[PDB]
Amino acid sequence: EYNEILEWVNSLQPARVTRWGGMISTPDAVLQAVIKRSLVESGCPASIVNELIENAHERSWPQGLATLETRQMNRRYYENYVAKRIPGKQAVVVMACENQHMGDDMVQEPGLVMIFAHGVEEI
Image (tube, rainbow, N blue to C red; front, side, top):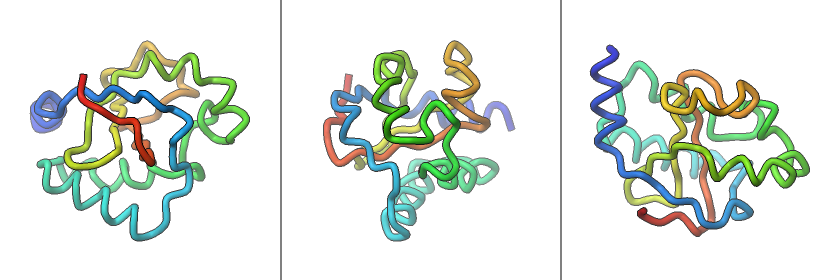
């Protein structure tokens, strides 16, 4: 299981989020399905694909990302996330297994997904 995930994660491109304010904290049902489709096509392991999507919305994000005011205050810390690009989308995955340096209020197992309106580019 570890290698499945490790190889999948390493195969993803490192993402550079240039506009943290462009985050979509409440993606609708269609956008959520779309990001899952992208994860599935990138070879995301079935053992975690559903958990990541659940964690692509506020209601499921860790307290460090829960509210808009908090997100505004914690912007400086987001620069330190080790983020991987979801192929073909303005979205990234933040895996717990490579973000231990962030607080437990900044990430959760197995990881989380952040979708943006724009500003996500390759490093």
